[PDB]
Structures are given as C-alpha cells and as structure tokens.
Amino acid sequence: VLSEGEWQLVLHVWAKVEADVAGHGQDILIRLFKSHPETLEKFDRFKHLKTEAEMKASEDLKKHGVCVLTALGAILKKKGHHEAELKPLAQSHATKHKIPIKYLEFISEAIIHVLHSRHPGDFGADAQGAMNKALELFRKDIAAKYKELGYQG
Ligand code: HEM
Image 1 (tube, helix red, strand yellow):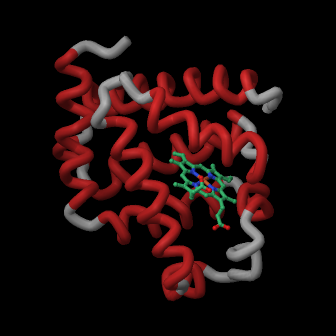
Image 2: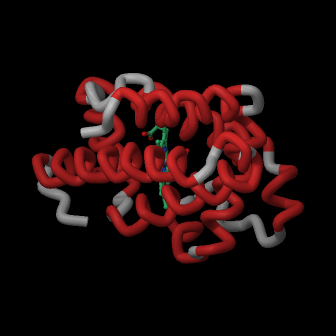
C-alpha cells in the first residue's frame, strides 16, 4: 500500500506526462523495444519497424502509446482502488496478447527511464521510489488477475 504522500509524488509526475502523452508513449515503447527486443515480437502491427526513425514516424505506434499511458494513468489515479480498470487489461493481456509479468517489469523499467530522462527535477529518489511502488502494486494485482483467468505468466 502506498502512503498518501507517495501517491501525490506519482500523480505530480504523471501530470507532467499528460502535457505530451503521445511523445512520452513513443519514448517508452521505443525504449522497451530497444532494451528488450523480444517484447517487439508480441506486436504483429509493429514487429516490421526496423529503425528508431521508422518507430517515431509510425502513427500506429504513437496512437498505441497513447492508449497504454491513458489506461495506466487511469489506474494510477485510483491510488490502488483499480479493480474495475485492471480487470479488462488483465483479460486482454493474459488471454489475447499473452504478456508475462517479466515483460511488465521491462515496460515499468522503460517508464521509469523516460520519466527520469524528461523530468529529473520532478523525479528524484523519493518520486522514483513512489512510482516504483505504484508499478510494483500494478504488477502484483495484474498477476493475481492473470491467475484467476488461468494464465501463469
Ligand atoms: C503498463 C503496461 C501496459 C498497459 C497499461 C497496456 C495497455 C494496453 C491497452 C490499453 C491496449 C489496448 C486494449 C487491449 O487490447 O487491452 C493494449 C494492447 C496491447 N498490448 Fe498492452 N499494455 C501494457 C503492457 C504491454 C506489454 C509490456 C506488452 C508486450 C510486451 C503489451 C502488448 C500489447 C499488445 C500486443 C496489444 C495489442 C496491440 C494491437 O495490436 O493493437 N502490453 N495494451
């Protein structure tokens, strides 16, 4: 469980993310695919993109980035009260996309990397700690919902 102060640090940096959702989304997905290339194999629409420049030019990848950060933003703003938001995401990611928790660890590392790169003055040790805790909570809760659906990834 995060403290109220921890949630405030998470939502303070998230407001900065919301000034440019699409640009954050692009940077996060590109960082994920660069750091952990096996994650790109999960994306039929995107696995054909071969360079960073093709990735940045893809309207499709940019729209996807917005849909990822919009879902994650809605979950974070519930401060842990996220069952109704998390359940459909678990359903699709367990049963259709088949995304293991280790891949959610990879995208969480990418989120932290981009937030630190873009907003270091609003993302110091205590804010990084808080965001790490919020994303650990997200991964714990989605793993439980994965298992309810019969997915052990
Ligand atoms: C913070 C973590 C994540 C969030 C919030 C999230 C959110 C979403 C959303 C909102 C969609 C569209 C609706 C849906 O199908 O559920 C989606 C689709 C998808 N996600 Fe995720 N996602 C996350 C992590 C990942 C990771 C790490 C992978 C793969 C390594 C992945 C693979 C996919 C795929 C393959 C689709 C379908 C994209 C398409 O073909 O249109 N997701 N994601």
